[PDB]
Amino acid sequence: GRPVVEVDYEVGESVTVMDGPFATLPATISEVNAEQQKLKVLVSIFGRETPVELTFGQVSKI
């Protein structure tokens, strides 16, 4: 178990997708929902930028 001093996500930060079809891909948190414990991260793709929503823990900080 490795606890982190900071456990809050914000917009503008970059995180790696850990769950979903983009798992294992660089993404940037665009919208976060602490009220519902949900997080949103936009993904950039060659002329295919598509926003994806995820839950806390589904992303790893770099």
Image (cartoon, helix red, strand yellow):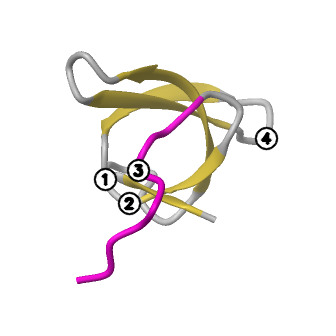
The residue nearer to you, when weighing 27 against 56, is 56
As measured in the structure, the alpha-carbon distance from the residue carrying label 3 to the one carrying label 1 is 10 Å
Quadrant in the picture for the C terminus: bottom right
Residue for badge 3: 7
Residue for badge 1: 57
Label 3 sits on a secondary structure element that is loop
Label 1 sits on a secondary structure element that is loop
As measured in the structure, the alpha-carbon distance from the residue carrying label 2 to the one carrying label 4 is 21 Å
Q: Residues within 10 Å of mark 4 (few under 14, many from 20)?
A: few
User: Which residue is farthest right?
Assistant: 47
Residue for badge 4: 46
Q: Is residue 8 on the magenta stretch?
A: yes
User: Which residue is farthest bottom?
Assistant: 1
Q: Is residue 19 above or below residue 8?
A: below
The residue at 29%/28% (across/down) is 38
Type of residue at label 3?
A: Val
Q: Which callout, 1 or 4, points at the residue further toward the start of the chain? A: 4
Query: Which circle, 1 or 4, is nearer the viewer?
Result: 1
Q: Is residue 16 above or below residue 1?
A: above
Query: Which circle, 3 or 1, is nearer the viewer?
Result: 3
Query: Which circle, 3 or 4, is nearer the viewer?
Result: 3
Type of residue at label 1?
A: Gly
Query: Which circle, 2 or 3, is nearer the viewer?
Result: 3
Q: Is residue 21 on the magenta stretch?
A: no
Residue interval drawn in magenta: 1-10
Type of residue at label 4?
A: Phe
Q: Residues within 10 Å of mark 3 (few under 14, many from 20)?
A: few
Q: Is residue 9 left or right of residue 55?
A: right
Type of residue at label 2?
A: Met
Q: Which callout, 3 or 1, points at the residue further toward the start of the chain? A: 3
**Residues at circles 1 and 2 in contact by the CB criterion of under 8 Å:** yes
Q: Which callout, 2 or 4, points at the residue further toward the start of the chain? A: 2
